[PDB]
Image (cartoon, rainbow, N blue to C red; front, side, top):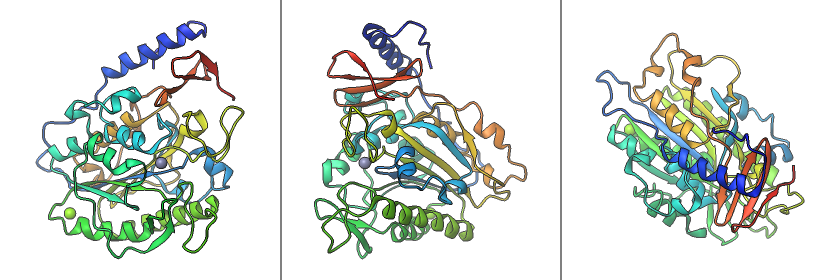
Length: 366
Ligand SMILES: [Mg+2]
Ligand SMILES: [Zn+2]
């Protein structure tokens, strides 16, 4: 996180953004060349959630849902760096390198930028899982072409449908998807796997079968958080060693502002990109006791990659005295810079600004 000493001017913010990109380009999440020979295998499950920010959860009265107190680690100031689904998945799939501009999401990146490819080199079977068919917005195509994720889509046949999207496509029940994930990872002939799971029940336009109005966001979120929390309980009981990372793509923009009305995401505003990220470890000999460890520093995907690197050997799952402080200290910080095509949002001296299509930086409503 480099200096914002100069007074805010459009030129100074342009320069700061350039310096941010240049500093980010030097950042890698470095993986070991091999695992220790006594490594303990485990499953990594990355749950990538559409349309979920702190602001949304507060608007829906779900800040105190039991899910949020169930995590071992929680990032209080994680930035999604974008307000669109495809870009958010690409950024997460490229978690192992510094944050790039929007444009550079659609240019190749170094192979060691690709989190799941880094894990594959260490022996983790890759799984791609979705609670939908990925057709809307060309999402699955972007996951494959720019996120580098070529794995077969995990079988979705016979999954119960809980919502229909705006396009009439199915939204599958997360409980059913996740319970199938348990079986598929058991049957994949590998003791370790890493799964990218994208789920969007909170998407705009989703409606119950037979009902034309889109379903209440709060109701869908309550059910989704109930299901995720109950899955955590099923997972604890399985005895299986699992690291779960819950990473929203971006908020649903429930609460608008003076510049951008509710539901619109053209501008990746702070309220849209400030998303809760949680990590929970299952099957530990010494499970984390007490309330989540809260990481307050500004964070983004690079911190997820570096956290995964820290536990690659799986010893966290068998240690008697886990050094949670060490595990959660010194993770990489990332300034809250967010981009879509031709819109960039930054915090400069703790105030947000927006720059659209190379116009001036405009103070963003606070
Ligand atoms: Mg397996
Ligand atoms: Zn999304």
